[PDB]
Image 1 (cartoon, each protein chain N blue to C red):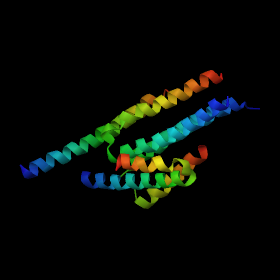
Image 2 (cartoon, rainbow over the protein chains, first blue to last red):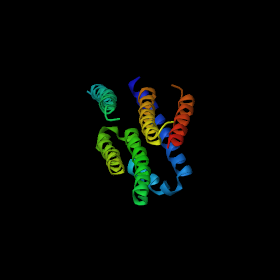
Image 3 (cartoon, chains in turn brown, red, purple, blue):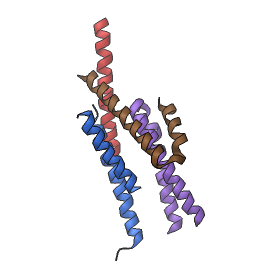
Length: 43
Length: 35
Length: 55
Length: 52
């Protein structure tokens, strides 16, 4: 149960930050370049 | 030991996650004053 | 005063960017998340300093 | 009338409260169905953008 919770929360967080990066790129193109680096800083 | 090692590692991950959650809650409770 | 205005705008943009990076840290490697948290607060604290001269 | 400096303080306080609520929802909800969670987070992010 703990492992399933960990996997589900990891998937949720991944989709959270993917959507947030996408929208930050969308409405703020000038900050698009660091955001991808942020992914490189995280992933 | 194989099952024991996996068991202990998964337990460590579990309460590490729980401690991280509690630390987040404590940080928000402390920092609400500075809000 | 335009310099302070643009400094505040770039600080707000950097604060949003650092919030995104910190929540990504929480997502992938939360164990060291605090390493950025106070950092973000410093920027917020700097914002308060930026209010002090505007008073 | 309300002075715009007081409105600015109210806006920043509401922004801080909104971030606190969003991260609390993330912390207490990570694991709720993925679709409902994603929709609620999209609403919260739209709220973040509008507050900005």
